Length: 73
Length: 76
Length: 75
Image (tube, rainbow over all chains, first blue to last red; front, side):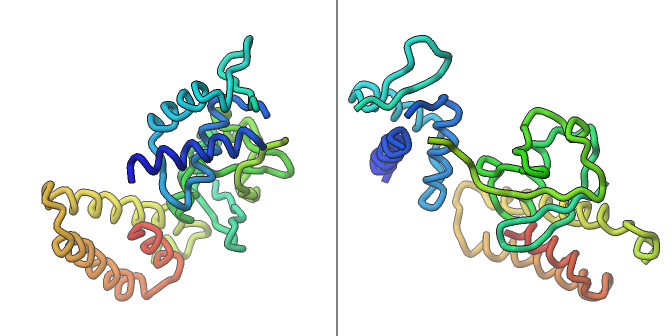
């Protein structure tokens, strides 16, 4: 299940980021908002997923912005 | 003061408040009564979304006042 | 009864009664160790429920607002 949550969390991030740019805090809260029905994700987990997503290059950070991410296709 | 708050079950709940209290606390009172995590809650006072770290006296909320609760809002 | 007579007397009492059962309940489970066996856990929670539910019935005369308080606190 633990691994599974990561994937779902990731799916949530991509899904949310698709629907363009969001601040880190906002993104996290939404992930919780979406995931609430299934389970409450640990904050630490989310952050890890976000980075994974960036490596995957699903989403990127804004060049000059405090904690902001853009959805990059 | 005791403020009334309209929930998403279609009812209205009165809760204990001090004007000096930060508004994020009211979210927790609403969790306690309605079982909705303060993480996902947004308080709207008369048309506008209430802040978090800002206090209730900053919004001039009185004991007759009424709050509306809605889930998170994002533009896109 | 004293508080009922005066206008808006009960709401403090509602929170107080809610804050209190919650502490006792939260404390009660802590007693039951890292075993996390369910039969003890269901039973401790029920012990507390039974004490207060009866208490709200007899003593407060079964007023709904306090009952809502209890439900939210037990959840």
